[PDB]
Length: 139
Ligand SMILES: OC[C@H]1O[C@@H](Cn2cc(-c3ccc(F)cc3)nn2)[C@H](O)[C@@H](n2cc(-c3ccccc3)nn2)[C@H]1O
Image 1 (tube, helix red, strand yellow):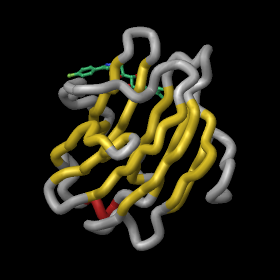
Image 2 (cartoon, rainbow, N blue to C red):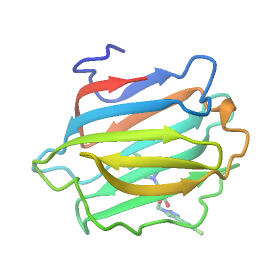
Image 3 (cartoon, rainbow, N blue to C red):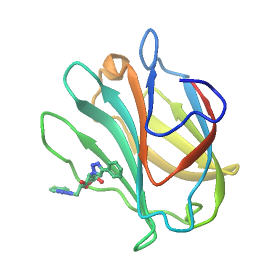
Image 4 (cartoon, protein in one colour):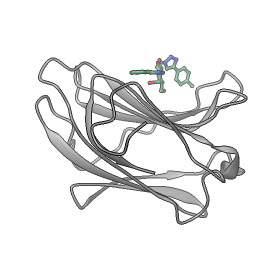
């Protein structure tokens, strides 16, 4: 998929895998009629999701979880701000740290997500699906 105006669903290969210090940029638009989209940091061969980010416009929630061997873990929903309202442009920054994913939206800290798949270098797929339009995705 291209870096600029990639269509959804976006399927991108993280070559060498998710290494520490790896920063993924997503700039995009939530349509006015959008219900939900997902960003998945996924182990393709197994289907596992180290980090799943699910903005849901219905209740204005930003749901974080992992899918590890067909099990959805505890949901993390705590935010100080929701930048994914209908008709909103967003500049999302996702850094894979040693112990935690670190996610900023429009320069403002959104959430931390402690690693659940400790072996996160096995993540080789970035996937963006659902009610989102993409202007730029940097892997
Ligand atoms: O906790 C995060 C997940 O919630 C799922 C709903 N759900 C949650 C649970 C659940 C069950 C037990 C738990 F301890 C925790 C959670 N069971 N079913 C969504 O289907 C699941 N999801 C949404 C999507 C999705 C894909 C493409 C576009 C938009 C959404 N894919 N998977 C994800 O949001």
